[PDB]
Image 1 (cartoon, each protein chain N blue to C red):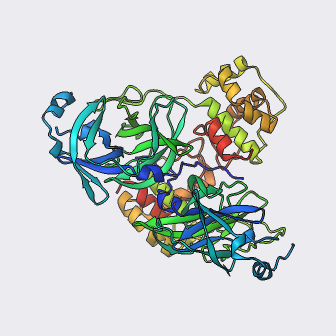
Image 2 (image 1 turned 90 degrees about the vertical axis):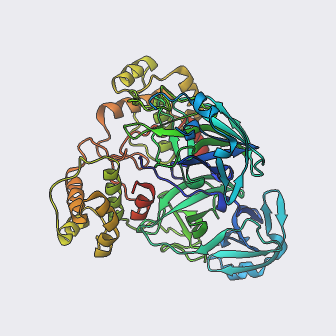
Image 3 (image 1 turned 120 degrees about the vertical axis):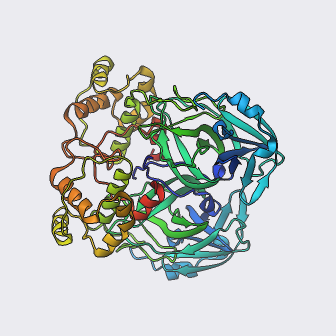
Length: 299
Length: 299
């Protein structure tokens, strides 16, 4: 029993974190096989930097890469979108089995916050519908990565690049392509309007039922269209039939039909919680996917 | 910016987790140097088990210890309070620098949830004033450990033993001494009454101010005694002068005196939050220590 925001064990990723220094900038890099990946903003030198010109002026020896207390020699450098690939003369002996995947808004992943190539903490977060993440990052955390783990394979999905003015965070996949309409140059860029991830809220209500919270349940059911008309009013994403299908296993385990739970959510949106809590929260939580619930909760 | 329930990177602990099987019971063990620590309830065979008699009837070969895909040979066994020490013929090459510390109610630690010797997730939690923890554990997680990390030293503080009827969790320090009035035998034992960890709530309010949440601040201050009279009414622990002193650095950084913040907390307890949130919560959060806030928040 119990339900926590749970991250994946971070060991396989810790073994890949290095420090990259160039000019006056120090940030984190990801060392896999004989390549170190890091944000291209480490490049020396401004409203519209031409990174291709700035990279042509650099040499391998400008890049100081430190893996623990061992310096790695850079033998090549190239740009891939907003990421820099530093070829080094040593393959990382701790390279796990890995993949570079890009995630969808509404999906979750673990973040290994790092500073000076040294991991400091691990936490879970979700890709928001507006392609920001509500992370916890201080100056120096650029290059920290987000990931999921499937049977000892690490699927890297995020590299951290910057903080937006609202305090939320933006970054790229490991091919260097930004999530969302953000750029690695100084602009007044700002997070767009966000929404609540409805399928995740429903998943979390199933987690609550699995864990003994039942006060929000009711005898009512709703149609998908009638639910979605209430969802739109409260700035919730539309619920699709695919969402309903994905919630099937949780619905079967609890014996509560998805559209039955939808009637509960409608009432919660219209009435609030009346001083009660669900899984230790007084808010409807939307950063747990159906998979996160199945993985963590009893079968 | 941002504030998350953040665990310590789990790699150093992952390298110590093993599987211990004896009889029909499989659970997790902690492999440090040439000793494997695990809950003594793995011993075969009941309302009042005499574990000393049950252990005398076991042999080294009854204990199957698996570290990854390598079996470890048990060459000795002994009891230490509610923990079993299995001496093995191989020292763990991944043993970190470590200590066995016992923590105080109100302190936090990271949990590495494990099953069959395989780590599955990492999360943060607090030792409740009633010596339970609100963990997330399924059958098979016994022997999973809790820890903090200080400059590459792992301070182990918790080994998981059981779930109480309310769904919360009880365990021991790594010397096998239970936290709280709980026993590793079948009883109607139940968590005692709990309270809210006041100094942590205040720390979290300072975190909120550091992160731009200011709506709960007011011009008022209070005396310590006047605050503590309101604390007792709302089932909050007393605030001591030591608590005030410990909050000093956060008070200095924000320029908000501790008793000034106490006046904010008093108003929040008396008025609620009026539909507003603090650091993404609609509840007053008490599982972040002053140290957790300083570590994670900007300086």
